[PDB]
Structure formats: C-alpha cells, structure tokens
Image (cartoon, rainbow, N blue to C red; front, side):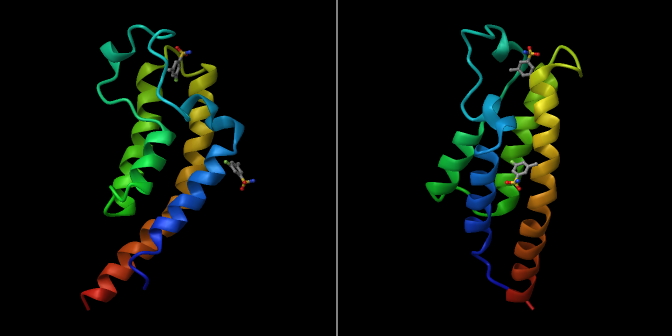
Amino acid sequence: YDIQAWKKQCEELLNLIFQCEDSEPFRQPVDLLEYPDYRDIIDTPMDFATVRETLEAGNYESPMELCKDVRLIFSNSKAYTPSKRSRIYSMSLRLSAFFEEHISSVLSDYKSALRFHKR
Ligand SMILES: Cc1cc(F)cc(S(N)(=O)=O)c1
Ligand SMILES: Cc1cc(F)cc(S(N)(=O)=O)c1
C-alpha cells in the first residue's frame, strides 16, 4: 500500500523502454526539419525524454498522468502515420503493447494504495 512506489516503478519501466530498439523513434521530439508538416497534424508532441524529465522534475502527481503522456506518444504515431504498415508506426504498436503489459500493475497498485489510505 505504498502510495509513492509508482515513481520508481515508472523510472524502471522507462529505463527498459529506452534500452529497447523499438523506442528509438520516440526517445526525442519528432524532427520538424524531417517532417515539416508535423504540427499541422499533431497538436501536442510528446516523447519519452519529455516523460522521463517530467517524472524526474516531480511534475507528475500520479502514474495515471504519466500513462496519459505515454499514450499520447503512441496516438501521435497513429495520427501521423500515412499507412498502418509504416516502419515507425509498426514499432509504436510493439512498444505500446510492452508498455501496457507493464503499466497495468503500476496503476492497480497505486489505486489500491490510495483506496487503503482513504479506508
Ligand atoms: C519486448 C521487450 C521490450 C522492451 F522494451 C524490453 C524488454 S525486456 N527484455 O527488457 O523485458 C522486452
Ligand atoms: C513521425 C512519424 C511517425 C509515424 F508513425 C510514421 C511516420 S512516416 N515515416 O511513416 O511518415 C512518421
């Protein structure tokens, strides 16, 4: 019932994501020189370095907020892809599956800890 445990759990999951080859296109903001109309399609850019920095700054209050930003990385890939068979989008789908598989217990444990605190 540790209400703070999610933070180190999210740091460890981000470390696993960073060291996976599939995260390379998502480690830093999308290059606007390479994709000059990116901001005509994507309203809110997001990347894993921004998520890690927000976490380390103490600017997430819960793992739900972190999870919303990570999901935004993946929805941005889905929205910008011209095809469901593109290389970057295919990498995003695998990385999303890995992230969802691992974030589920982090969210459940945190919500259970908050419920116990308010019992
Ligand atoms: C499929 C996958 C993705 C990833 F980012 C990290 C791992 S591992 N072998 O470190 O658990 C596995
Ligand atoms: C930034 C980005 C994301 C994505 F999913 C797909 C593309 S591409 N190279 O197919 O235009 C570009």
